[PDB]
Amino acid sequence: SMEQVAMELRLTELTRLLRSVLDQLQDKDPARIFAQPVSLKEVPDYLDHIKHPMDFATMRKRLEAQGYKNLHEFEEDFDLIIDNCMKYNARDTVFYRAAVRLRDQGGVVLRQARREVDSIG
């Protein structure tokens, strides 16, 4: 149908906007602490601690399959990255600190993204 196509154009444009959001968030992680999945070879107990691991490469695979229906689902995954880290790592670690800084800096980007998504529909 023509409607399914219109719908698919909106999802594609949302994907376009979320790809830009993802790039902006990922720039706030210049150390690349959050770039890839925590290695289960190197942290073999990780899944005993963290039940839903997340990272930027995994979000990108979902994004490129148009697997985010709305900004809320995208933000859920970004929050997992931060929240998993702040639980697994202690406060005095470079990892915890990196998550706090990503959260704080990401807030600005996510604030305007929400306005853009509501605005453009």
Image (cartoon, rainbow, N blue to C red):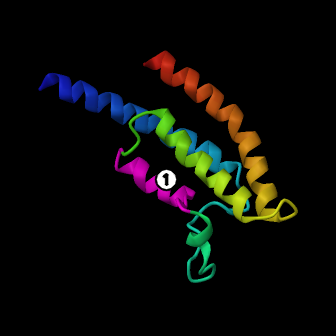
Q: Position of residue 10 (x, y in %)?
A: 34, 28
Q: Position of residue 11 (x, y in %)?
A: 34, 33
Query: Is residue 20 positioned above or below 60 on the image?
Result: above
Q: Which residue is at a point 78% across and 49% down the rendered structure image?
A: 100
Q: Nearer the viewer, residue 31 or 51?
A: 51
Q: Which residue is at a point 42% across and 56% down the rendered structure image?
A: 61
State yes or no: residue 58 in magenta. Answer: yes
Counting labels gives: 1
Q: Residue furthest right?
A: 92
In the figure, is residue 20 to the left or right of 87?
Answer: left
Query: Is residue 20 positioned above or below 55 on the image?
Result: above
Q: Which residue is mark 1?
A: 59
Q: Residues within 10 Å of mark 1 (few under 14, many from 20)?
A: many
In the figure, is residue 1 to the left or right of 80?
Answer: left
Residue 44 falls in image quadrant: bottom right
State yes or no: residue 118 in magenta. Answer: no
Q: Nearer the viewer, residue 88 or 69?
A: 88
Q: Nearer the viewer, residue 49 or 9?
A: 49
In the figure, is residue 120 to the left or right of 49?
Answer: left
Q: Which residue is at a point 15% across and 23% down the rendered structure image?
A: 2
Q: Position of residue 5 (x, y in %)?
A: 20, 29
Q: Quadrant of the image for the N terminus?
A: top left
Q: Which residue is at a point 78% across and 48% down the rendered structure image?
A: 101
Q: Residue furthest top?
A: 119
In the figure, is residue 62 to the left or right of 88?
Answer: left
Q: Quadrant of the image for the C terminus?
A: top left
Q: What residue type is disc 1 on?
A: Met
Dot 1 falls on a residue whose secondary structure is helix
Q: Residue furthest front?
A: 48
Residues drawn in magenta:
51-66
